[PDB]
Image (cartoon, coloured by chain):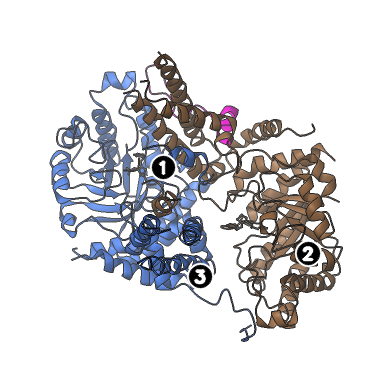
Chain colours: A blue, B brown
Amino acid sequence: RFLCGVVEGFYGRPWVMEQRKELFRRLQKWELNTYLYAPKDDYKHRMFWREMYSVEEAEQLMTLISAAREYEIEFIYAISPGLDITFSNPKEVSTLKRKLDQVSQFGCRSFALLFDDIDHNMCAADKEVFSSFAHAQVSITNEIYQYLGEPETFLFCPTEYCGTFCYPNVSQSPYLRTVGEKLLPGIEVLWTGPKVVSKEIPVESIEEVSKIIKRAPVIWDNIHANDYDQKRLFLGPYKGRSTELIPRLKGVLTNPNCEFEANYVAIHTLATWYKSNMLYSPQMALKLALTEWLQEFGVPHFVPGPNEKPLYTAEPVTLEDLQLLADLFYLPYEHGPKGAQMLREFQWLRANSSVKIEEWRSRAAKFEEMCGLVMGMFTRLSNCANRTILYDMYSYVWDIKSIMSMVKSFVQWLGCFRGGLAGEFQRLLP
Amino acid sequence: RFLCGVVEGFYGRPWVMEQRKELFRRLQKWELNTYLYAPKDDYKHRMFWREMYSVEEAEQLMTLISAAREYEIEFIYAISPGLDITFSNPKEVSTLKRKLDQVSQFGCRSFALLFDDIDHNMCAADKEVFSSFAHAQVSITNEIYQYLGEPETFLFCPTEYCGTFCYPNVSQSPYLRTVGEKLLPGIEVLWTGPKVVSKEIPVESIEEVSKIIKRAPVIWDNIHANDYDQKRLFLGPYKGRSTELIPRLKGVLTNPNCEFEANYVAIHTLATWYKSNMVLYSPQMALKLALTEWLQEFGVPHQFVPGPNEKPLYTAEPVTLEDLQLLADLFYLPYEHGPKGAQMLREFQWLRANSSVVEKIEEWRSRAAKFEEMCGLVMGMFTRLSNCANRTILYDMYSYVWDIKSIMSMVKSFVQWLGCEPWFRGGLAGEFQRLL
Ligand SMILES: CC(=O)N[C@H]1CN2/C(=N/Cc3ccccc3)SC[C@@H]2[C@@H](O)[C@@H]1O
Ligand SMILES: CC(=O)N[C@H]1CN2/C(=N/Cc3ccccc3)SC[C@@H]2[C@@H](O)[C@@H]1O
């Protein structure tokens, strides 16, 4: 009973109901099975966790939950009361149960209590009735598991959800020790890897955590999350997670890009990786993902003479175009092959600038040609028929086209306020 | 007859019909009078200028154009054919004519043709039939003006639509000379001033262009546009345009931020500037007037009281005027940070340079702490924005305020460290940008 799919768990503009339904369509298609509802800035999920859904909100959640049954996706409703709750106060515990009862009434079987990204300092009144912070969470958590009659699927995200976040370390964490002991064994535990956005989730780290968690954890994977850096998109494939981890985990839910339509690769290649050992090749999973993704660009959501201006809209998006895009907007820790290369070629064309000086002039002329592929990719994308995809990635495609059209003017100049205030500070740090 | 209002004229996700109706309501409330429709990447405005509106698209346009009439806002439909039209071919001219006649039947009485951000190089058949790019544009433009019955308002936007873009200068541009000579006299010409994004629009610069084009232009103002730089947002006031320009202009249409709800200040301050001259206009007082009005929208969607022993309500403190004054100073104008933003940059420039002395080590200890306080007001500003009841405004600004909150907290912990991986910020674009 392995939970594998998508947590809508990021900061900023949540997905709307139309997009979530369509995500169910895509999860079923690729043979994944779980959706965790946890959008940090959907007001009633965290900031106003006490507030009851209105009739209109109730109706849209009922329809969305129905839509998840219709596509054989398990809908897990998460709630985040960490910022605000007095755990010792029973009227608070009552408020949380009322909120979770309304959601069961919408036809929701599965649930989650998240405690991630809050400070570990309790109030005077919780300090009295509870030993440590973990104790207070485990109490509230278990009592809710039980009140809801021990559902099959009931997740718990600890405040210490990655390696780095464990004080003083993983295996001697007194917050985590208490989670493995006092928290009921039917409740599952969420974990992001060594770090918040793990580069790798190695098997050593999962055995280690399991030992003190005293369970196989559900992985909350932030590998493709772009909520933390305005300029960054992640179109690269699932990587740094081995097929070997599947038997050591109760599940893997990926928290991908804020822009819905850019999670084709992230959610596709994750399915390639799950099929693999229910072995896995990143560079092949991606070509598989990109080839199918290319299908959507041509579906919405004169034949000029030899003396006449040719059609600007003539050329359509091509698997090469998309392959470049993905290399430009790859992963949180490596650029794609063509990306890291364009970069190197620029570093050297800048250093060895030479006022056998021919190795340069017909080497930075292969660059003026490769900078024109970035420009070509934007122009064809700006003309594609699926405007929904374009709009979702417009800001990012424009940005990289702009920096490469300025890097071009430069690496062809050597032969003859950008970012606002945030930028001016950035350019004065490390 | 002065056209003052908004042009939806920018690259990227256009506004949806609900937002446009909301715009007309705001324009009327602030006593502005014009909307120019020209979204670079709305489907059938530019790339697919030729295709006619579906029956569904036609219903939406008609509802929008009636909404404009109901709100006493002039609706100007613009089209951008110059990427791939052939100007000599009377079938291409007939397609353009068809497109505009369709919109005319939707209720539209005002039109525009735009020839901006296309390359200068014509093709063979056009080169044969027309003397210059200007000759071709003036030709099909004058035709269309006359076909639609010489409507009271019809705009032209040149390929050479600012100073930097005129070859080889404004005064001696043969392109603009052709436009001023040939282009019919009842058509108005749009101008972005000395630059695409003009810091100032000096009156001298309006008399210069007015001569080579032989009329008072209509400004297309890109002062608050933010399509060109992913990290930028402009919440500062209308600034750098004398009220002396008004009597020397046919109008001002501002092309503001992509994010609809970030344009309260941009549009509100333009209104104040316009209305001040129908020292008349202070940007700073315009800005306070706008943020004061804007603040009221924040606590409106688009009980347990804890004891002294218990955890207080995270969501308790609502957005203040001082929070919005800080936000605007952080995201001000294209060529100027606001006072608090410049100040915060100055005290950090200095704490970094005079770092050694950690005597004058009595000063630095004070300064670094007053700086930690200010970084604190940026975090507090984020926290209260993310709790506000208007999730629509929050969503449009989220990524901007998240970013300045996260950079100020990096900077704050660098200044703390000097007194002693979410956290390669920018991706690939980043690393290329750091070599220029
Ligand atoms: C349980 C979990 O993954 N929660 C978060 C983690 N995270 C972030 N957290 C905030 C943070 C900022 C700076 C440094 C560390 C942590 S940002 C990316 C992701 C965000 O999508 C996600 O909901
Ligand atoms: C008449 C007019 O303003 N047209 C355009 C100009 N412009 C831009 N031009 C593209 C450009 C990119 C790079 C360098 C120079 C120019 S971006 C801002 C604005 C954009 O909103 C607007 O539609």
Q: Are marks 1 and 2 on the same chain?
A: no
Label 2: how many residues lie within 10 Å, few (<14), some (14-19) or many (20+)? Answer: some
Which residue is found at the position 29% from the left and 35% from the top? A159
Label 1: how many residues lie within 10 Å, few (<14), some (14-19) or many (20+)? Answer: some
Residue under pointer 2: B107
Res. B90 in view = yes
Q: Amino acid at mark 1?
A: Lys
Q: Amino acid at mark 3?
A: Arg
Q: Which residues are magenta?
A: B304-328
Which residue is found at the position 15% from the left and 57% from the top? A244
- Subunit that carries the residue with mark 3: A
Q: Which mark is residue A380?
A: 3
Q: Which mark is residue A40?
A: 1
Q: CA distance from mark 2 to mark 3?
A: 34 Å
Residue lying at the far front of the rendered structure: A356
Left or right, B212 with respect to A260, comes to: right
Residue A178 included in the magenta stretch of the image: no
* Label 2: element kind: loop
Residue B327 included in the magenta stretch of the image: yes
